[PDB]
Image 1: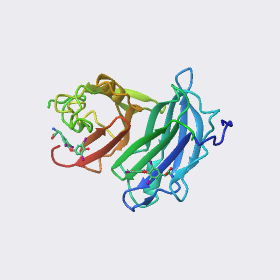
Image 2: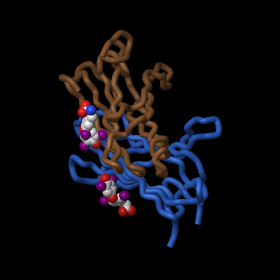
Image 3: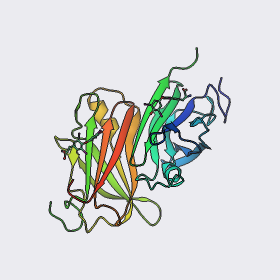
Length: 127
Length: 127
Ligand SMILES: N[C@@H](Cc1cc(I)c(Oc2cc(I)c(O)c(I)c2)c(I)c1)C(=O)O
Ligand SMILES: N[C@@H](Cc1cc(I)c(Oc2cc(I)c(O)c(I)c2)c(I)c1)C(=O)O
């Protein structure tokens, strides 16, 4: 079930790909925020992508309550590190989570220096 | 377009397309912000896409100085009018505007209910 600050059924996963190199985007920083009652963004979780370009264990079912979340992906530092000066400061994904019960969320991002695409895969959890 | 203190020399243009229907995304709101001293976001420009999914005359070359800009596109509103339940609260594009490079910026967004792609076209010539 839940847990409380780690990785329940993995309710939140992030996957980043590099469209220039045809590979996972490794060591990409990220930051997740939750909108608090006062309308500010409070820190919720952060991590870096693995060699497979994925980030797991950001949260648990218990901690991942109903709310508005923002996933910031630090695309700028990734590209600079490669010798490329990209267009965007970062990629942001803002969505309401769990408003009709708990769901599992996969945020995928595909990166190019002047372009990014993002998609969400939402699953009604556990089989 | 005209000019003065921001609004029509076409240094900045937004184009929004709908991938479900294969058309321009019309009457989409957006809002442009410029980052200020205090690291907060100051209103800068706003409008709604036209019949061709475009927004022009947001600023002028005199007003468009070097800085960090954020373009926020009200995608949630668009999909709700179509009776489709979207994933994203909105789409956000954050970039640095630099005098060195080309002077005309085209920001294009391709919208789907659970996905969006954004690209920047930076040029010397015209749109
Ligand atoms: N281990 C995770 C990793 C993973 C998720 C997705 I979602 C995916 O599919 C796409 C398709 C396109 I097109 C993209 O631009 C991107 I990024 C990801 C792929 I490959 C791998 C999983 O499988 O659970
Ligand atoms: N009247 C404007 C309309 C317009 C501008 C662009 I730039 C464009 O090109 C792309 C390509 C892809 I691929 C996208 O996902 C998107 I959104 C836009 C298209 I089509 C139409 C003009 O012609 O001036």
